[PDB]
Image (tube, rainbow, N blue to C red; front, side, top):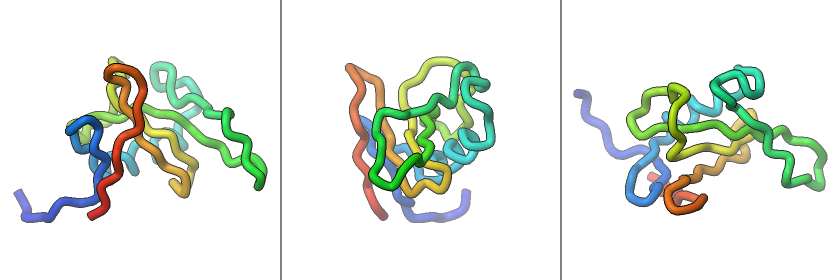
Length: 103
């Protein structure tokens, strides 16, 4: 394939979740009605902000770059529409925040 250096990614217990994957998942989350993609996206309303509503959606991610196809959930993103908030989590062993590795 084409030569490329590593892009920014989230390290989820050793598995890299690429920025392009996360971006695509947020785009799908915000172009899909809540719950419609096999239960997702869901709405995170648990962090009211001093600046008012800023709708945050939760949506599954995959390690493959393929869009999630409705099955198990090992990784997920919580983000606003323009990704100004964007965090990635895993579920293995209990929910944990993945580590952003900037490249």
